[PDB]
Amino acid sequence: QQIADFDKEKATLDEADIDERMKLAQAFNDSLNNVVSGDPWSEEMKKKGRAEYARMLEIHERMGHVEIPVIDVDLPVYAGTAEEVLQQGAGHLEGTSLPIGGNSTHAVITAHTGLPTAKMFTDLTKLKVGDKFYVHNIKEVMAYQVDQVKVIEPTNFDDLLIVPGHDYVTLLTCTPYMINTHRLLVRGHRIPYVA
Figure 1 (cartoon, rainbow, N blue to C red):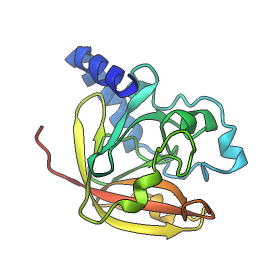
Figure 2: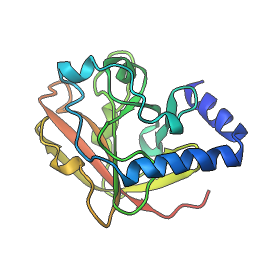
Figure 3: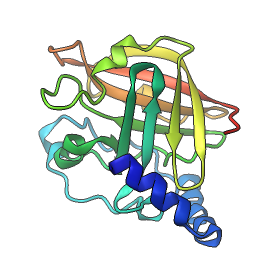
């Protein structure tokens, strides 16, 4: 329904509408203030208001979905990382690039581990270097290949920032499983894709 709704509606968008929206998204990325908003699981971040910064990419509030076939994940992605968003799917980390790719871009997509009700990113620990994931947006599907998995403390954002000369997406969750004192970062680099 959620992902289904996005793909169906995506298919109905006029190409000129997509062109306008992508212009706005590109401009946002090109001028990005690349400073990580905060640790999504902190009280200050959980209680954040609605996020409006990605409206150009949104169909019914969803800016796309993240598909990880090897662990049977396909989650809608919403703007920001407020508690309500992470209850519903994945959240885009404000301060990171919008998920439209390009050289010198780094988008971070966040979701829970260990929610009793929905698996979300629980199986991120199963991912291996070389595994693929796919980021769907209003324009296209982008392929990424995992090249680095690491564990960090929650307020260390160094590995979440743009690396000049690379096109990265990092999938972010809490770790270890059922301990949650740290964060797991699964980073992929962009690879060619033809649907």
